Length: 125
Length: 125
Image (cartoon, rainbow over all chains, first blue to last red; front, top):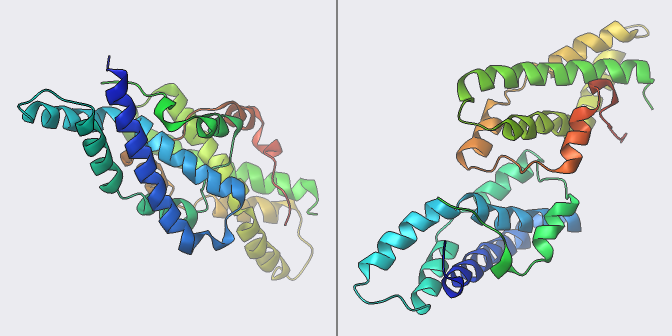
């Protein structure tokens, strides 16, 4: 169960960070990509944080524990931003383009894309 | 644009071969996976063929011409069988498995999974 202002800061940072990378990769790989192909690669960012939240959570915690002081939302932004910067997604984007298995844009991918990133639903462990 | 007699024979064989690679992958990467994941993955087989069918069409227009005579459907069944074995989907299944990006099971995907092989929609180019 986790406190909203922490959870949200984690989110806003991580997916924003995954999207800068896609914005950098697309400047040079996107010449041939339809809009719904470019928007399928933004869904992949959002879903990536979903399938990896619990793994990121063990690491957030042991660090938040290591602060000695109470956590303020400020250090949830910093850890969140440090995952956004530290993950290699172009690898993923390359395998999907290279095997032309960039997913087919289904209605529910746009359900996840129309949402404001602080709201993308995750689960736990 | 290909008499459906032949196109049906390529599909049944392509997808069949792709599935014998997946049941044999599942036979060592299973208990660990929910049912919907084993079925997102069957969609991946179908979809891969819909997204690489132009590359099958170039290779089959070529080795059909080389026949020296009119094809009948059995020439199809053999080249469809073949396109179905000289792939190793295992690496594709494993990057979705390690990078925990097996696709989320969505509506459209079980409509394609419901369809007899012989009817999986491929558009001609």
